[PDB]
Image (cartoon, rainbow, N blue to C red; front, side, top):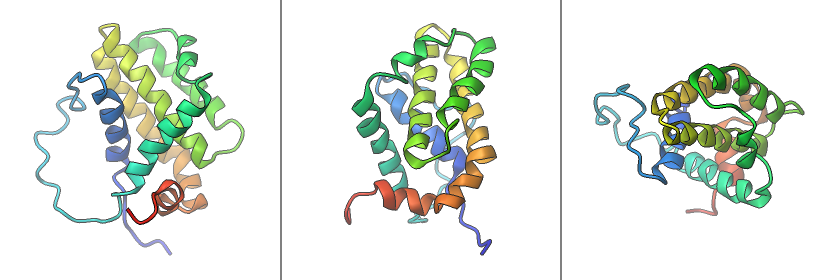
Length: 164
């Protein structure tokens, strides 16, 4: 019914990478794309379990396979003039066969691997372009399916705990 209640698409993608990257400690902060983080007011109650879950599913799933994705990142080259194109291919195959929650969570973890790889090879700035590209596809093609499957509310409930 149209309505309105965005879930911070830009914050959802950046948040995921912020955590997956934090594992190393390398202070990213997106990239001078935010003076401070006070503007946000203590409210919403619509993205407290969706993130926790989405962030969990990635590990619970990515760890389940441990065969592709992570190591699969070796295929792609390594540079700002590479991730761009390759990104399209990698993602293309991700949802090549219909889109689904589990498939989405996989798309996230993937982007996180490519990013960390940049800062590893002295390509920190590359991590910025990554988070961006991902965000795009997220709202571009994923948006349609997102609401189709039930929207964030569907995600949170799907991979969300049991009253916690």
